Image (cartoon, rainbow over all chains, first blue to last red; front, side, top):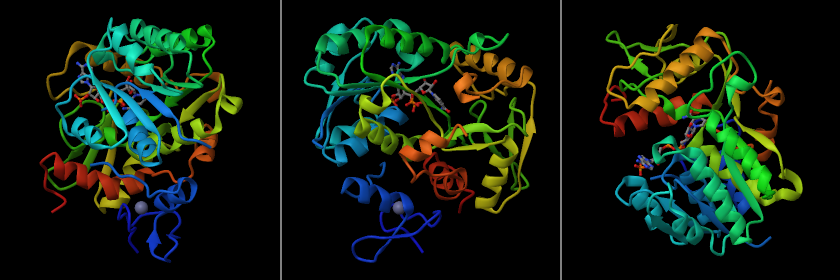
Amino acid sequence: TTCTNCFTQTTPLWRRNPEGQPLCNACGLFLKLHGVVRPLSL
Amino acid sequence: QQKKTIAVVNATGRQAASLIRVAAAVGHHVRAQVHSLKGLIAEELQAIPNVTLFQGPLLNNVPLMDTLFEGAHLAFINTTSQAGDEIAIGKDLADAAKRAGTIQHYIYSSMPDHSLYGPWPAVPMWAPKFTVENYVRQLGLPSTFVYAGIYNNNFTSLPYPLFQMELMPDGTFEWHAPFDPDIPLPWLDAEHDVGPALLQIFKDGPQKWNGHRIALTFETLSPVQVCAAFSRALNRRVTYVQVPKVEIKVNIPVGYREQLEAIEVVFGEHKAPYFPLPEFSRVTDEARKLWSGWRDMEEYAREVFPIEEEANGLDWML
Ligand SMILES: NC(=O)c1ccc[n+]([C@@H]2O[C@H](COP(=O)([O-])OP(=O)(O)OC[C@H]3O[C@@H](n4cnc5c(N)ncnc54)[C@H](OP(=O)(O)O)[C@@H]3O)[C@@H](O)[C@H]2O)c1
Ligand SMILES: [Zn+2]
């Protein structure tokens, strides 16, 4: 699968946002803990 | 509970930039010091809503320092040798912070002074930080010290010292360094994990972390394993080669040359620990507890390395 935030395809554990949509451990975890989507460089 | 205002210096640096992005994103206010507004990162940070930049030098610049700490409750301080005497600077900053009187948590990014734990030399751009740490402790500032592992993104196929993932003609990759190939080194993904971790430390307060040293490393790999990782991601033959000296294929300024020389001796000659501190001699335990969404070498190599190359103007990923 591919992460909807950072678009990675390599992750120790996949996640589901409040929409069942696919997130990576990082993106999903960050959102869960802080409330906002993980901010990406660039 | 409430989001605070964070003072940061060297905003464009990989550690600061990481924190800044995440800090601003969750609602914190950021007062940051940048040496120049010209630059990709600079403009990026310039763009983030609740980020205020102050362009000027840190060396003998107390005025800026005072401004930077006005209304600040937190601070993440991580200097560079490019700015000058890292101790005169690190001391002034800590004094500024104390004068402000509103800092609740002052996280300083520190590094070891190897000549204090063995017959080794003091690595030029690490040891001075350790002196500033002690000074922060001295002032009594509620603090926590972080020791960053070596960045996964130091890697590049370009002719840059110590961390060149060289693209051989036959399409294979080779990494030549003084590091022992079997000895695990502390790694860290600066952009991806520094921000989240520092956030979590701030979120915990000095009530938990005051006076503590934390190893900002999420995984330990031996040169061979690093290569086995790049080789796993790019599906190419990546091999490590231990060389007595650091190869310097381009023109570099003194400080980095001296720095590398010391590295040759400490890691090549003496086979010494990146973190010669008794406390750091798993070291990844605390870091992983603070942030469990870390990015390992494999994902870096696969997901980022290629991209970064591309941006640097390369094309083997095509
Ligand atoms: N790489 C590793 O593996 C590793 C591991 C542990 C600790 N560290 C420590 O990290 C520190 C560096 O911090 P970092 O990684 O966040 O930064 P960094 O990403 O390595 O970037 C270096 C920075 O200094 C700025 N700079 C360039 N010329 C300058 C000048 N003349 N005066 C002032 N600033 C100047 C650059 O800004 P512009 O891009 O805007 O010019 C850039 O942000 C060092 O002390 C190093 O020892 C590195
Ligand atoms: Zn993601």
